[PDB]
Amino acid sequence: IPFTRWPEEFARRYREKGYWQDLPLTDILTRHAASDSIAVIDGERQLSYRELNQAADNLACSLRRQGIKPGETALVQLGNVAELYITFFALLKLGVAPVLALFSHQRSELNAYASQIEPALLIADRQHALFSGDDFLNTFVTEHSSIRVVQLLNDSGEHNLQDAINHPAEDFTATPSPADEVAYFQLSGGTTGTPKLIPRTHNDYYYSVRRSVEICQFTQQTRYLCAIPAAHGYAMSSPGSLGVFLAGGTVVLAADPSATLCFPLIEKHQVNVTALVPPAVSLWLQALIEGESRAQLASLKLLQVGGARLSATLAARIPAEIGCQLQQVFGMAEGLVNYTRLDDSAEKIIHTQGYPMCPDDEVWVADAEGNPLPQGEVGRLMTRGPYTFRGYYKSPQHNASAFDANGFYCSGDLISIDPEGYITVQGREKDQINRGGEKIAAEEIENLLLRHPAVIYAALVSMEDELMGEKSCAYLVVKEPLRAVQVRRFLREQGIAEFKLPDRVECVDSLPLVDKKQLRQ
Ligand SMILES: Nc1ncnc2c1ncn2[C@@H]1O[C@H](COS(=O)(=O)NC(=O)c2ccccc2[N+](=O)[O-])[C@@H](O)[C@H]1O
């Protein structure tokens, strides 16, 4: 499985310093294979590490019997369910590298992922609108003929993922890919018209988990509510569910971050850490103001907030109104994660997005033409390090633009750095809407909009929104009367995720040739 390797001297350095340990990610789970302590709670169901590890072996073995081989790829679509983890470790034990699509993703995204990786295996959920029946499947399996095996959650027929999980593995020996090879693909937020895959090796990903575990001080006491989409990197590895597993703690799954669901789960299971995006924080604080008892949250000791910028105002309300500590988390699927620390001053936790997890994360600030700016100045975030990728999957064209000659990746973020070394996110350069933490590549939606018979020109831009931070607005130059609901129906027909439908549509007589900078003015 081809990907952009680190130069040999970076690998060597990163091994000498102890960052790359050459262990497979399966070791996160198998070190606890003998443990009957609880690893995952999902509704009424509670799976121990022993059971979780056996479930991954069973599924891996069953897939091996059905002909899946090491070095092949898979497409996985599972929400906040225990079977997400069973599947991730089962594929890791076989040396198969998955994309974990989010439940919210639809045809265009699944098609895009399948087209790039040519999965031999599709695993999905009949609860998803696309898979309750068999029509889409037939089309998907026809148009992506690489697929030989389909397993489905909540299925009673021949393709029931449970039957595979429940079938005891006879004589199963794991064959994880080598540690310096690809373990899995992450999804980028998106800055272009087609989605970009981020290969993650075992060395690089395990280090990001292990080190996030030291910084967040996770242990067997950790009881972690995973309420945001479980397959996103923030939920998975920063320190996420995998850091919880590493530490031997417990992951509590929630379908969504609503107070309605989560306040009760936090009290019931005595949750002590969770991860949210800013709007979920506001909604929580407002639920308390509408009279939810603060005591449901007593056991909470650490609340991470990331995905998008937390305002200082909102941040300060966390210790005050919830009474746990805040940790700001500014990371990216491509790699780099900055954290505020648990012993940082209130000033740094409230007003900054922390600093890199690794001492050899290298971060500088560039001006418009690639030159370093002195500290305090606002510019483009440039970075490289032991867990930051060196290229997107099969993307020579885009890769040429995304990295400088020295291997530094530009995140598209505008930042400034403190005298103390802390980073503050000041804005953005990449053509991306950050809708309450969820990323929308504007070019993707614009291209879809231009396919409408009536749309001549199209621009998608963010607009300030108090709850979500940013909402999306589509500015269109049109031939004929066009209402928002027509645009949304149409985009939905193209088969994209709901959060990607414009919150607002506006027909305008003209747009500048599209020069969005001009448009903002
Ligand atoms: N804390 C933050 N403040 C302002 N912007 C933030 C932020 N955290 C993430 N972002 C933005 O989100 C982009 C990364 O997008 S992402 O691939 O969906 N990943 C994440 O947001 C993320 C957030 C926290 C922890 C881990 C990740 N992650 O690597 O998945 C960054 O380049 C920023 O533009």
Image (cartoon, rainbow, N blue to C red):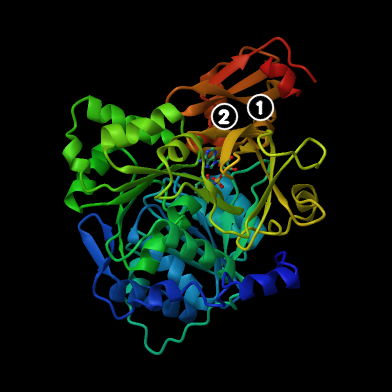
* 485 and 168: which is toward the camera: 168
Quickly name the residue at label 2: 490
Q: Residue furthest bottom?
A: 171
Q: Which amino acid type corresponds to the residue marked 2 in the rendered image?
A: Phe
Q: Position of residue 231 (x, y in %)?
A: 46, 54
In the depicted structure, whether residue 210 falls above or below residue 392: below
* 87 and 480: which is toward the camera: 87
Q: Secondary structure at mark 1?
A: loop
In the depicted structure, whether residue 129 falls above or below residue 165: above
Residue drawn at 31 percent across, 49 percent down:
254
Q: Quadrant of residue 42?
A: bottom left
Residue drawn at 27 percent across, 62 percent down:
221
Position of the N terminus, as image quadrant, is bottom right
Q: Quadrant of residue 427?
A: top right
Position of the C terminus, as image quadrant, is top right
State which image quarter holds ligand 1. top right
| Pointers 1 and 2 in contact (C-beta within 8 Å) | yes
Q: Which amino acid type corresponds to the residue marked 1 in the rendered image?
A: His
Quickly name the residue at label 1: 452
Q: Position of residue 226 (x, y in %)?
A: 35, 51
